[PDB]
Amino acid sequence: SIDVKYIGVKSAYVSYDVQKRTIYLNITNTLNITNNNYYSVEVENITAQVQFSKTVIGKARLNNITIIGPLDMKQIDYTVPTVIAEEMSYMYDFCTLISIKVHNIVLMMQVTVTTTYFGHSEQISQERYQYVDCG
Amino acid sequence: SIDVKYIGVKSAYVSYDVQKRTIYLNITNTLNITNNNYYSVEVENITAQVQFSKTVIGKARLNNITIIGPLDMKQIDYTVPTVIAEEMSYMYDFCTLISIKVHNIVLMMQVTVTTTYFGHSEQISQERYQYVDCG
Amino acid sequence: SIDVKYIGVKSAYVSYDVQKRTIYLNITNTLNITNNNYYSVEVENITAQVQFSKTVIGKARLNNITIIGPLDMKQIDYTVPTVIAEEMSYMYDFCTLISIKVHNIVLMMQVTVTTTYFGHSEQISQERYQYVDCG
Image 1: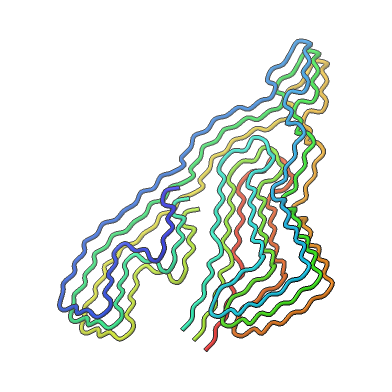
Image 2: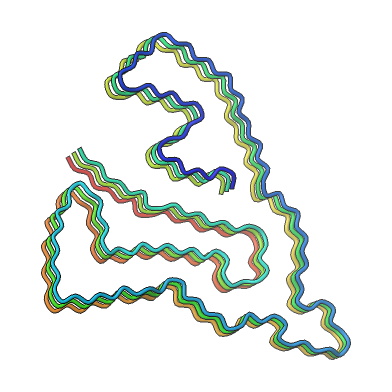
């Protein structure tokens, strides 16, 4: 929640890149760095009171105070029908990266049906580093 | 929750890269670094009171105070029918990375049906580093 | 929850990379580093009171205070029917990485149906480092 960085190739604080037919003679680098980070995050001071019926007296009557009624969820529900009378295929793959009719699903329910959660919740996802190299 | 970095190739603090036909003569590097990190996160001071009926007196009556009624979930429910009368295939793969009709599913329920959770929850996922190399 | 890093190739603090036809003569590196990390996380000071009926007196009556009613879950329920009258296949794989009709499922329920959880929960997942090399 401070630096969520998606970096393509490289990351550094001090970086020297010398490439591809160069000449680099008798140089004099001198760094006098002072890099201090003082993080102080999420310092919370909470004080909560969550009653549904506080101090009910005197011949009263309550009924259906908190109703979360009929609930229905259908998160991922899809249909891929296929009717073919005749089919032919010819794949001639080389040094490649194929994916045919796969189903890549990721689901993350952190705090589902509940009551009176305190504190801190956190979900992170970063997946499928795929790669192909040839020479 | 501070640095969630997706870095493609490399990461460093001080990095020297010298490549591909260079000459690098009698240089003088000198680093005087001071890198201090003082993290202080999530310091919480909580004080909660969660009653459903606090101090009910005097010939009263309660009923159906907290109802989380009929609940239905269907997270991943999909259909892939297939009707074929005649089928042929020819794959000639080489130095490749194939995936045919696979089903890659990941599901993570951290705090499902519950009541009065305190503290801290955390879900992390990073998967499927795949790779193919040839020469 | 501070550095959740997905790094593709390499990680370092000080990194020297000298490759691919270079000349590197009589250099003088000198590092005077001071790298201190003072982590102080999740320092919590909790004080909770979770009653469902605190101090009920005086000829009262309660009923159905906390109902989590009829519950149904169906996490992963999918159908892959297949009807074929005639089928032929020819795979000629070489130096490759195939996957046909597999089912890779991962499920992690941390805190399912419960009541009054305190403390800390944590789920981590990172799987399937696959790889193929040829020469």
